[PDB]
Amino acid sequence: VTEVEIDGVLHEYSTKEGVQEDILEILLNLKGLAVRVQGKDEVILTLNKSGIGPVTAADITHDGDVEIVKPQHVICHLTDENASISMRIKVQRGRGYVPASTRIHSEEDERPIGRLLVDACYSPVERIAYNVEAARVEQRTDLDKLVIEMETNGTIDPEEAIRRAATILAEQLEAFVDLRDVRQPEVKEEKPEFDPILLRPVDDLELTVRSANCLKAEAIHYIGDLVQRTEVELLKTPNLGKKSLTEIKDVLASRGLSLGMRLENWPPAS
Amino acid sequence: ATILAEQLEAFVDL
Amino acid sequence: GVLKIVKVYLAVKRRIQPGDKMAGRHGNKGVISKINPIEDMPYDENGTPV
Amino acid sequence: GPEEITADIPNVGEAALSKLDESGIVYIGAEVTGGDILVGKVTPKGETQLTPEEKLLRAIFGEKASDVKDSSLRVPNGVSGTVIDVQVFTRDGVEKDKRA
Amino acid sequence: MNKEILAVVEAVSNEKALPREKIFEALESALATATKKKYEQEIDVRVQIDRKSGDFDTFRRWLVVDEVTQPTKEITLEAARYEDESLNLGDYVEDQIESVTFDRITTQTAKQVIVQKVREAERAMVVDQFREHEGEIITG
Amino acid sequence: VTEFLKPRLVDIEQVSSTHAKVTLEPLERGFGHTLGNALRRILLSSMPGCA
Amino acid sequence: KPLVGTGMERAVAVDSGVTAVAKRGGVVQYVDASRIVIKVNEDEMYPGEAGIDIYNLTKYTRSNQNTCINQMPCVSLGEPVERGDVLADGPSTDLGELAL
Amino acid sequence: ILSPANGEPIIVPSQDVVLGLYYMTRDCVNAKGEGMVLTGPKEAERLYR
């Protein structure tokens, strides 16, 4: 789990009337909770529960693409008759271990106050013991059979984990299976300075669909074609009055571009 | 590297 | 001559990092030096690390 | 002049006033960072104009827009974290605030 | 809002220097300069506060020119098709309505514009008031 | 992203034409040790020749 | 808990303040993450005061060294308790044992 | 690398390396590999690793 949200609470340093543990304990148990996603790479799980008793993993609203590895894992304890919790749980697939601090990417993702960041610790393996032994080779001597025991979350599959690790090793080894003096730096690159956002349709500039059909009323999807189109073709563009024209003037000309700029290089290569 | 890769070859996928 | 004292609180989940100061109960103090990856710490034959 | 804790700040942009509430205090949970505005306070800055022809203007038409100054409590530079609680001690006589 | 500015021009001592009409015109100028801060968009906002009838109604100028920089105020020399504009130059829109006429910076720039224009007007008055006596012994 | 990092090696120094020094960069948090140790243990013992 | 203790831990925990120790034994009527409500037995009660007594466990609260204090409840629900038993571990305490 | 007080060297390997080198330079009377001949130091290093 990576991001949780409980409707009643604001910050994980609070409590909730009815749950035996604090929100901090709930988050730690959640981190302890393991799950196996199959279809997608990130998913959202809703857990609703009411009534006295222990809330465990099985109680969450499971899906088909998602499977709880073990349901008996206790999440919290409701200790009142009319006490209830509903919580959304973001579960994303990743490699390794990322703390809650550095995972921030912008200055508005946390702005939803109910979004509690649980520092993700996703690694199915827990310990890997191994040892060599005398393999019962049909006719040879002192060949080695390697016995590897993995204590894991049960999430990953043992043979699958072995084969994945071996693939990783082979891929990393392919680096110097054919090593030679190689350098990615190729100084003095040569590329046309056409801006690639012009290749996209105009509607990709975060505005409504009526203005989209409006720029589809002049048959102008391209930004690389609208760039040769000043404001001399807007009130003449079908149904561009105040509101849709306000959208056109706001979301386009503010992103650093200009509504119609003369250029001689287009389109390479659309 | 070649000897190790041809040892590994029994497990990898691609 | 004061009207409204507004006190605000701030909490930090202060994690551990190379540089803190930890000690046992016998004066064996010490600065933590490296968060070594789990696959590098010494480990017992039963696979458990230290 | 007295000190008020109004939500509006004369100069700063929308970001620096986004965390606060309608009264001018951050909500309980905004993950502030060194520099942000907890409150939320303005002070009577100016002095010595002595033009009652303009004092009559800014006593009714600019009653609270005369001598602003953003001596507002910012989180010290460096300390981040989460706001978890807000206490408000109001001197009696001084009426109240919504958060209070 | 409108009532506030009416109370201003009532409390305005130099009512001859600035009666209700030019008072509210200067206040529309101040409101445009305030919208200049409300939006990072630098748009000429005529308002026409409806000096005595009722409250204000913000508009948005078009600054007729073949340019599109700051498109809030950009219209070519014939773009008057929708809205039944039918005007090449001077055609200005009323897209955004009901901005703020009560906050801190609004009233601060109101004070600034008022004092500036009042002092300018009294200066321009006294200039001719004393120029009348051109060719007389004056003190000083 | 379940896709790792591959090195952009920087130098194959061939001092004395029989004592080389290869550098490799960059490798993941621990892959340096595992790759170096595996290569070393294979080259030392299990690397056929004639003598 | 510390695995190798000196027995003094129970005494130093219960004799300090950080733990919310029960006053009169009885039944744990209602336990939450912040409140505890005990119904005392018939022997140690008075004519009035039907028997319930409440412990408001101080949640995350500042200290004179700017470190957190908190009294999570250690007892379960409905479990009978006797006089002078730890009902909530304080900061760095486990089941009434000093655990730093 | 010398104290201005005494002409002694200030860069002295204090601990945790003197232990290392000292362990590396001793002699068990009967240790695995005793009694061989080595064509050089690098050969001994390979023989050890």
Image (cartoon, coloured by chain):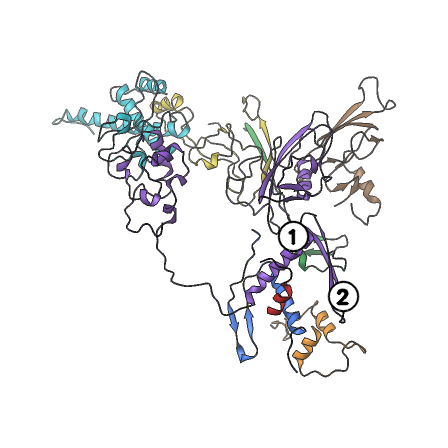
Chain colours: A purple, B red, C green, D yellow, E cyan, F blue, G brown, H orange
Is A84 situated left or right of D72 in this image?
right
Quarter of the rendering occupied by the N terminus of chain H: bottom right
Q: Which mark is residue A135?
A: 2
Q: Quadrant of residue E67?
A: top left
Secondary structure at badge 1 equals: loop
Q: Amino acid at mark 2?
A: Ala
**Relative depth, front residue between A93 and F26:** A93
Q: Position of residue A269 (x, y in %)?
A: 35, 52
Q: Tag 1, which chain?
A: C
Left or right for H21, reference G49: left
Closer to the observer: label 2 or label 1? 2
Residue at the front extreme, as displayed: A138
Please give the name of the residue rendered at 78% of the width and 45% of the height, measured from the top-left corner: G1
Q: In this view of the protein, which residue sits in the foreground, D6 or H30? A: H30
Q: Is residue G25 above or below residue H42?
A: above
- Pointer 1: what residue? C20
Q: Amino acid at mark 1?
A: Asp
